Image 1 (spheres, rainbow, N blue to C red):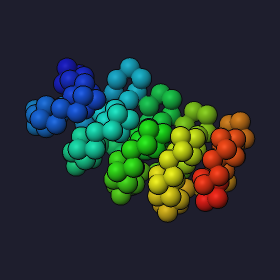
Image 2 (image 1 turned 180 degrees about the vertical axis):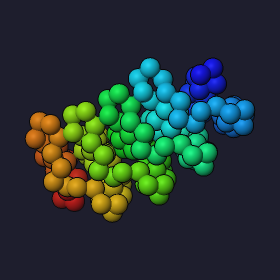
Image 3 (image 1 turned 120 degrees about the vertical axis):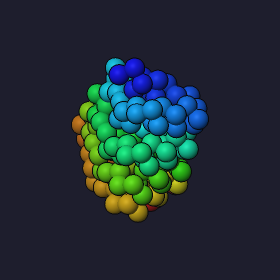
Image 4 (image 1 turned 135 degrees about the vertical axis):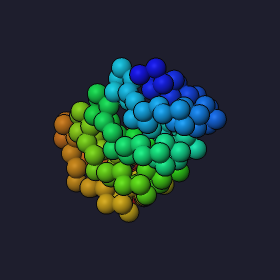
Length: 154
């Protein structure tokens, strides 16, 4: 896909004009890079909320999986992008998606100390008992990290 690749680069760079143009031209909204990441993954990871929004309005798969088993929500949560987390959840992101090692969005947000994100994930139904492949819950993570404020709510 010539235009899938340009869309991926434009989404990552936050070039909202180019994104709009490529989608108008007919670029696949769920185009993948060589890691299995779609434009929605790339924008969710880097933190371009306006790109996330427009992709989602153009029918982007909110629960697309890359080769590591990560959904956009995983990436936005891990990187602290609270507004992206909120919009992904409003559009039906799976709050309890588990990646290749069983990390959920709650594990990832707890591990990076993002309290506000943890709060919203919990509201959307994140499973506080979910273990990753090594047996750790989000709560365990919070104790390992010495983060007392996280632990309280987890």
